[PDB]
Amino acid sequence: NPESADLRALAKHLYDSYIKSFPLTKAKARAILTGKTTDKSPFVIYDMNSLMMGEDKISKEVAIRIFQGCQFRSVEAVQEITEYAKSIPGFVNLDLNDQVTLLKYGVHEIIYTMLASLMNKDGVLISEGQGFMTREFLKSLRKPFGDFMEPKFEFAVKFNALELDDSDLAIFIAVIILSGDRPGLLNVKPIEDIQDNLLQALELQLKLNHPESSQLFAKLLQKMTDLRQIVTEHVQLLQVIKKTETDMSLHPLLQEIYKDL
Ligand SMILES: CC(C)(c1cc(Br)c(O)c(Br)c1)c1cc(Br)c(O)c(Br)c1
């Protein structure tokens, strides 16, 4: 019926621009990870030598070198997410400062939601899925660097259990961006009206897409406490790095997001 239709229409619209804005979807990710024939097997990096062997395609010192990598990829993700946000009906019509504020707080929560897509209990796709880097290798890195990925993996395992597909996530990450309770928002109300609409998009999306799945909407919403969790941990992890590795550069775009989080 006409309300549903309007919401389904919204669902399709977001799935479509989500596909357009993100080169490594979950569907691709799982094909690579599970061993399907639509895609290519990843090289696997499980230790120092394979790191060195993987290098050739796919300089300070390993742990820092890997870390810098995750960060540069973060910046790209920020761009990806920024382009996607623009496609969210009403988003570019907001106060410019709120648009900025929504992204400042939004992108990390979204980065880790989608990073889940690239993860299973044993490791994570890198270099656009050409690589795979195992959780143990990471966890093995010289502290404090052995610690930046574990909390991600932890969330990812819980979260991947919900069994969401890209078309569920497209709406979910829209919901995240359009969070009216962000620090310093000028006009909360129009932000809430859009989110009210996205939420309704999601509630229907989940019920149609996952009908046997009880209270998935509620369960998916509850997952945001985990996101903020790992997001704050990360910035604590960074305050420490900055403190001990004063020769390690940090990207300005990322310095902007990190400040006063
Ligand atoms: C390691 C990982 C998953 C990563 C990405 C982001 Br964004 C992060 O913020 C954090 Br922390 C880790 C990644 C994924 C892809 Br695909 C890559 O091409 C590369 Br190079 C690295």
Image (spheres, rainbow, N blue to C red):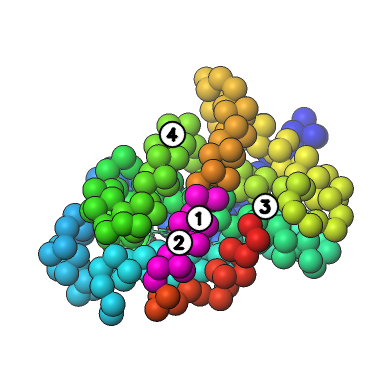
Q: Which mark is residue 177?
A: 3
Q: Please tell me which of labels 4 and 1 falls first in the chain.
A: 4
In the image, which is nearer the foreground, mark 4 or mark 2? 2
- From the image, tell me which residue sits under label 2: 240
Q: Which mark is residue 158?
A: 4
In the image, which is nearer the foreground, mark 2 or mark 3? 2
Rounded to the nearest angstrom, the CA distance separating label 2 from label 3 is: 28 Å
Q: Which mark is residue 236?
A: 1
Q: Amino acid at mark 3?
A: Ile
Category of crowding for the residue at label 3, using alpha-carbon neighbours closer than 10 angstroms: few (below 14), some (14–19), many (at least 20): many
Residue visible at 87% across and 55% down in the picture: 187
> Does residue 238 belong to the magenta stretch?
yes
What x and y, as percent, mark residue 83?
62, 65
Q: Where, quadrant-wise, is the N terminus in this rendering?
A: top right
Q: Amino acid at mark 1?
A: Gln
Residue visible at 40% across and 68% down in the picture: 244
In the image, farthest residue toward the front: 243
Up the image or down, 155 lies above or below 81; here it is above
Up the image or down, 86 lies above or below 215; here it is below
Q: Amino acid at mark 4?
A: Lys
What range of the chain is rendered magenta? 231-245
In the image, which is nearer the foreground, mark 4 or mark 1? 1
Rounded to the nearest angstrom, the CA distance separating label 4 from label 1 is: 22 Å
Rounded to the nearest angstrom, the CA distance separating label 1 from label 2 is: 7 Å
Q: Are marks 1 and 2 in contact (CB under 8 Å)?
A: yes
Corner quadrant of residue 85? bottom right
